[PDB]
Amino acid sequence: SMEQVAMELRLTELTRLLRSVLDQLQDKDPARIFAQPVSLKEVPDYLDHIKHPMDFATMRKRLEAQGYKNLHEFEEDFDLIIDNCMKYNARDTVFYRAAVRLRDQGGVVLRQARREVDSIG
Image 1 (cartoon, rainbow, N blue to C red):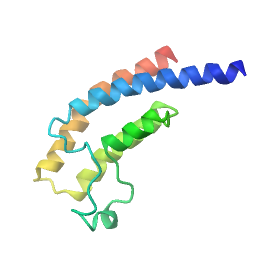
Image 2: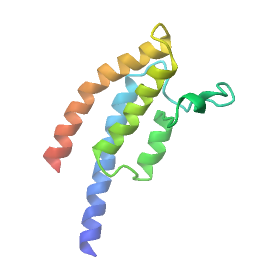
Image 3: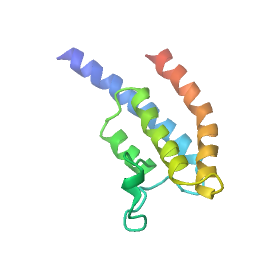
């Protein structure tokens, strides 16, 4: 149907916007602490601590399959990256600190993304 196509164009355009959001958030992680999944070879107990691991590469795979239906779903995954790290790692660590700085800097980007998603529809 023509409606299904229109919906698909909306999803494509959301994907375009979330791709730009993802690039902007990942620039706020210049150390690449959050770039890839925590290695279960190197942290074998990880899944005992963290039930829903997340990282920027995993989000990008979902994004490119157009697997984010709305901004809320995308923000959920970004919040998992931060929150997982802040639980597994102690306050005094470069990992925790990196997550705090990514949360604070990402807030700005996400605030305007929300306006753009509502604005453009």
